[PDB]
Length: 222
Length: 396
Image 1 (cartoon, each protein chain N blue to C red):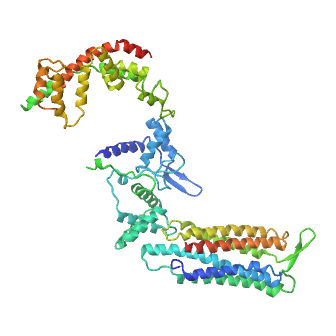
Image 2 (image 1 turned 60 degrees about the horizontal axis):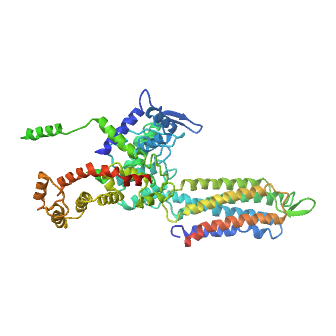
């Protein structure tokens, strides 16, 4: 825990707790409030898990050189949170954008989200999409791409617990699973009752959440 | 110093290798990613070997190339571990200041210098592999005092070389990378430095007498030696268990035991009996031959001289604790006149025996043994091979 700061880990764990919301969400009926909170919770969870992880690894690289040259504490745990809040902010402005378009134009006037389609001749309601969720996905993709380059070069350190293995594999796993999930759900606007979807969200969440709790946390009792 | 000559020969090799008129051409490749000059492909060097050396086996020429390339005379541009692989990969010769023939010896501080320099040229990645990162960790933990001027001269060198043109920095850093591969190699491949600790380091009257002994040094023509060598080959040529063995039983190859077990059986095979017929010396080497020859000598009431010679040989085996105990006794039994076993001597023979018998010696009865031995070799063995028992035993 001294090798890997307390507060980073409480941050991670809290954030991902929150990322478990998509699947208490859907059990309740879809409405306005539902899909919106979904996007809030998702994106908060996402950055405040994968982002901070990637930046921890950046610190590894810098402490290395710092230490090779003159041990003088180049990067500290005090440095992480700052290059966190930046990202937290950006995402706040974004949510405000989307949330504004709804809450000021298409709230009551012309459009809505609580909305259903049909399979052959039978009914099913849900939330739904537009182009925004597309761009969202593509951002997640690129972000972790940068993280992967980081966990590419950093492959040779003499280090204590080989955290790099563990982190980097969470990263790769997540990228993959996310590509697939989003691709399916963003073809499948029409062929989705509640159940089949709820399958899909259950998959994504327990997969990456449990994974990227465990890979880092648990081995730190062995 | 021995290996010096080895390196000299291989220097001859590479000198003929980068020949002006002949030689491999050091090309400049062009790629969709980059344009790399002054390299070549391992198939080139393989072809060069096969041409100018006539190394019939591709594998043999490849192994020669392998160890040459593991002595730092050329390296693969993208690898640490020196190995020549016949394919399209890019190589390079080495510099006359960085051969291995120049008695070079790096040391730990200098490894630290090269580590700091490589790690600090680029600062995009830990441009290294796990073993070298491991070595640098230890160098850190043990070199607590002395680091600074290391870092200093490292980046100094970096400026002094980057200041020269961009392809120059590349080729010089490639060379002075590989030359430290070879002198501190990856954990697996063998070092090619070390050596074994063994190599770790009247006057004219005697002259004239040497000349005279060369004169009386009886020699025979090489053709004579040729016949002797060919014939000694032939007479067992059909016994060679590598070339042409009649007993195909091979306990090594064909998972048999019977061949040696027949060899343990005292009954001689027909090979054995034909082989006895060459020389009684080989017979006496054979225990079986000793037994059968001795049987004939007994039944012919002629079992003494062999008894003597066996006595001499069995005497030449014990330590200095029993030499006197036997020599006097053996004299009193054979060489004392009046004993039953009557070995028979001439003047100088019995004179030598009487003079030496006071002093038990490791070469006590040399002339007497010669006398009786030429006797037996001249007489006994002939009639034995001519004997009915020999013929009946050789038939089957």
